[PDB]
Every structure is written in C-alpha cells, then in structure tokens.
Length: 102
Length: 93
Image 1 (cartoon, rainbow over the protein chains, first blue to last red):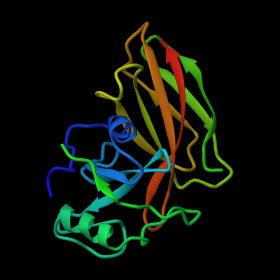
Image 2: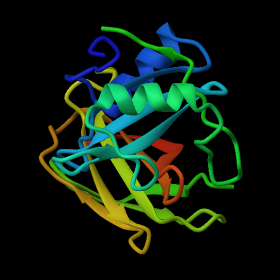
Image 3: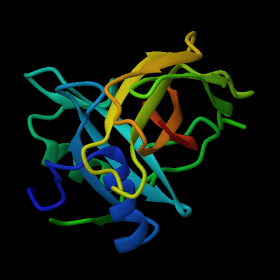
Image 4: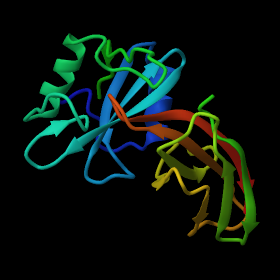
C-alpha cells in the first residue's frame, strides 16, 4: 500500500533508486511511460533491473495473465506471497523481497 | 544473449537523431527506448515502445550542443511480460 509506489519517476530514475538505495530483491511500482496508463514493477535482481508490465483495464490489474486484482497492493502482496511464479525467459526467478518506499 | 548490439546514431541534426540497432540472438518481442540529458539521472527523460520488427527510431525535440544518453531495452512476452538487458550510448547534438 502506497509507500512503494513512486508516481513521479521515469524508468531510469527508478533504476538509479534501486541501484544506489536498494539491494538485490528491492522493487517498486511506477506508472508506465511508454504504455499509458498502465503500470510497471521495477525489480532489482543480480545487480541489474528488470521492468515488469502491469495491465490496467480499468476494472482490474494483472500481468497480462494469471490472477486479476482490484488494486495494485493486492497484486504486489500476491506476488510477494507466491514466490517463484514470476520467471524470466531463461527461467530465472524474479523475486519481490523488499519494497522501496517513498 | 538478449542484449541488443551495435546501437548507433546514423543520422543527426542539432535537434534530432536517427538511431539504429541490431537485434540480439534471442529474438525480441518489443524494444523500449529511453533518452535524456546525460547527468540528469533520468529526470524528465522520454520513452516509447516499438515492436520487435522495427530496428530504427527517430528522436526529436533535442537541445543543440547538449550531451544525451540513449538506451534500448529488450522486451519479451510471457509470465510475466518484461524488459531488461539495456544498451546505452552517448551523443552530443
């Protein structure tokens, strides 16, 4: 809820936050700048930053598949609790460990 | 290897650039391009998306005589849909 959502940053700003103020497993949510008005989950993993698309249909949030949520907070909580569901193309597990606040 | 290679400015004006890049070995679904003044750390940077079939893009509205950074990510569809492995270059208009 609230704190880990950063409304006024770009993708590069998000990376700099994660790469200088967070650790491996840190993440935040932010508005998509290339797909308005969707959302992006920027996650730091292995010294790099992966950006994940969140679909906002106006009725629910999801990741273009899987469970559908009323709010962003429910989506994030779900994917923190269900560790191991989110994977890269090679099979690398995307881990949502530490929300980066403010 | 999902990192795009050979990102270049192949045409330039004081206010605009035409960039080109070669596709990575792992075939891409889409690219994400971001750009902004070097040193600004991402403040007020612009970004847009193009499909994986496109390997060129035009960037406009640039200040003359200013250092810019240009970054291209590789994006994939799946569970989840994501983009990463960026490539960056610098260019002074």
